[PDB]
Length: 24
Length: 24
Image (cartoon, rainbow over all chains, first blue to last red; front, side):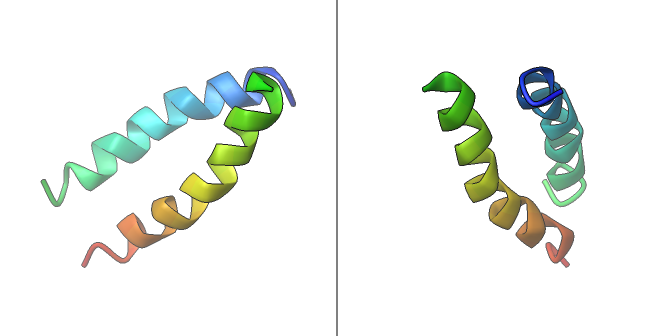
């Protein structure tokens, strides 16, 4: 939610970090 | 405000997050 999503997106970002890593 | 600051920074991240897709 508006509060959890902030933190949740942080876990998603991890995946985003996992993505950049493809480069990396 | 962490709530607004993080969610806000995310907006800034979104853009960065967008670039990664175009890595590529």
